[PDB]
Image (cartoon, coloured by chain):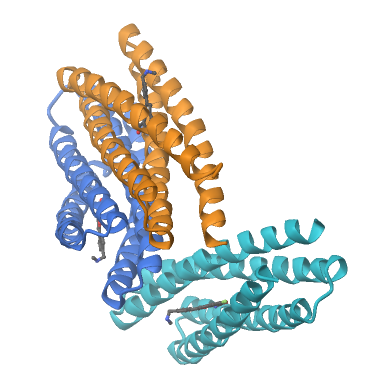
Chain colours: A cyan, B blue, C orange
Amino acid sequence: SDAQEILSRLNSVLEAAWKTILNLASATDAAEKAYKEGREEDLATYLDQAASYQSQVDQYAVETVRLLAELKKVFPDEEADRALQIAEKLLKTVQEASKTLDTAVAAAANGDEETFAKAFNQFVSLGNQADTLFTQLQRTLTNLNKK
Amino acid sequence: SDAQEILSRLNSVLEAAWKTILNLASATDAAEKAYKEGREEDLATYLDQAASYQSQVDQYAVETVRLLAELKKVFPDEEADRALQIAEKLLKTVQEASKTLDTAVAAAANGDEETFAKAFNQFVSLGNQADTLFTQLQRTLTNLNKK
Amino acid sequence: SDAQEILSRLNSVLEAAWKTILNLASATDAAEKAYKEGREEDLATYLDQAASYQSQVDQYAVETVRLLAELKKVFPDEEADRALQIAEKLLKTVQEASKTLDTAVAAAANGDEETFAKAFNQFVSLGNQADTLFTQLQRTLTNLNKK
Ligand SMILES: CNCc1ccc(-c2cc3cc(F)cc(C(N)=O)c3o2)cc1
Ligand SMILES: CNCc1ccc(-c2cc3cc(F)cc(C(N)=O)c3o2)cc1
Ligand SMILES: CNCc1ccc(-c2cc3cc(F)cc(C(N)=O)c3o2)cc1
């Protein structure tokens, strides 16, 4: 059916997103280490890398919202309705993480440790919020792949 | 002169290689964390990322040898001889790191932890040896770029 | 089921690997022609292409082992054991080819043809050994799939 193609694309998107999230986590940890070690050029590179993966996560979140809305049209189900609401909250949260990472990038560029520390801490907290949303989404998708 | 262009290309290669090495370091640290935490699927992702960066380092290390070989050909004396010798030892070490990382990746996929740990720890040690040569090469090239 | 997902991903990986293997074979033949003709810059280009394709084959071979390892966990039988054993031997052989190509690429960059030619011919032999295992694995997966 159409529903099966959409679910297959969703599965591929969430698989790719999970890899990107791992890359984002690695870059973020490397930025934390460079920050603690006072290696400003390393920190700049790793913030740029984190931002790149963050932008990709943002795009996977967009694509997930789009695909779930498509699924609701061709295969109505309160579970797909549920996944879409989670996916939309995830999209809001990753965008908020991007904004805070951008603040951290600008603060590092300006050499403004006080703004940097607040922004970087908020980024980490938003990442955790989003990871919690991502896991709910994965389990809703599993409950959808078995219907 | 041909020499100016070559030294220029070399500085660009080494700057790109340094970025890649930072990515390889972040992925290696993330693999170590996944390994400690027993998160096998995460470890697989990070090992694949490390292998991809390591392949890119290998390519840059090849290009560096080729460029220094070319620079030596536009020299009537043994001036670039030492830079080339360093770069060839760097390449040898980088390729040993690559082989050893491959052994680690296979051992992880095979679920052979004894082999994995031995190879992963060897890879880390080869990376530090390679880093010593990389920095030595950069210093030698500064002493050539003055003209 | 999980089984059918794994088997479909495996079929896709092996189809992609087969194309990469064809690309590797063509680059290897082009490198041999450039070597015989004495065109060192062409040889460098083709060796770099070969190395890139080889790194991709290495990754697909790792993915194939991981997928068959997963399948054996879900159905612990002899056919799953057989397929995994073949895939692990394929991976070993591919990594041996990869290390041998590394030796050849470095020798060509170092201007050491005696080492290059020996290693290049070793690489070709290992590639043909890997092809034997690759076709054996395809035959084993027919017994695992159509079922
Ligand atoms: C601070 N320790 C490293 C770290 C950093 C970020 C995250 C993380 C997970 C995650 C899951 C998502 F679905 C979205 C994001 C995001 N930042 O958009 C995530 O970040 C996890 C660990
Ligand atoms: C284990 N802590 C992370 C880590 C990993 C690798 C390296 C490293 C540096 C380096 C420099 C080179 F010139 C080549 C390589 C390489 N592996 O080819 C390097 O690895 C540094 C830190
Ligand atoms: C074109 N005449 C040279 C030649 C012949 C065969 C190959 C070859 C086949 C093959 C199959 C695999 F499954 C893996 C590899 C590899 N090198 O990893 C292969 O290489 C490479 C070069």
Q: Is residue C96 above or below residue B22?
A: above
Q: Is residue A114 above or below residue B107?
A: below
Residue B141 appears at what percent x and percent y?
Answer: 23, 44
**Viewer can see residue B15:** no
Residue C16 appears at what percent x and percent y?
Answer: 52, 38
| Location of ligand 2 given as a quarter of the image | bottom left
Residue B85 appears at what percent x and percent y?
Answer: 14, 36
Viewer-nearest residue: C78 or C19 = C78
Q: Quadrant of residue C124?
A: top left
Q: Left or right: where does residue B79 sit relative to residue A28? A: left
Q: Left or right: where does residue C129 sit relative to residue B136? A: right
Residue C75 appears at what percent x and percent y?
Answer: 42, 58
* Rendered residue at 49%/67% (across/down): A48
Viewer-nearest residue: B48 or B112 = B112
* Rendered residue at 45%/81% (across/down): A111
Q: Is residue B89 above or below residue B77?
A: below
* Rendered residue at 74%/59% (across/down): A4
Quadrant that contains the C terminus of chain C:
top right
Q: Left or right: where does residue A111 sit relative to residue A97? A: left
